[PDB]
Image 1 (cartoon, rainbow, N blue to C red):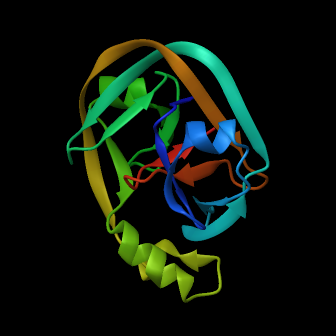
Image 2: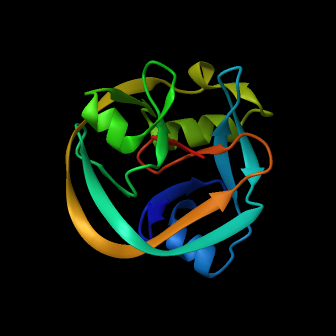
Length: 159
């Protein structure tokens, strides 16, 4: 699950915190990646307010952070979906979208799905360390097709 303020890249509004999307049950679309490495958009189908649990702030090498529960999965540079704490524990890297606005603009001009690498580029980002934020509100969203979505920092979060 993700912290209230964790921003999801929405098609209609750009970066929007998941706590806002869930608390207001905002009907918007996220960007997801399919098995063929293509980006496409999908409308949120479920909005989950998961109560409160321990949230850790993972510091990323590019200066951004991921405030999430230790078991939340992300796509690594070895193309595996792993809990963020396991990615930190094993000194692995997150496979992330590089130029957010550039890619959003490119995709706006194509019918989707469209290959990620033909509308953008990836970066390899290590997870430097983490600190506890203590118990905080947490959230999740459910999608009808692939169970992943892009965060505002380019990371690929998944079920």
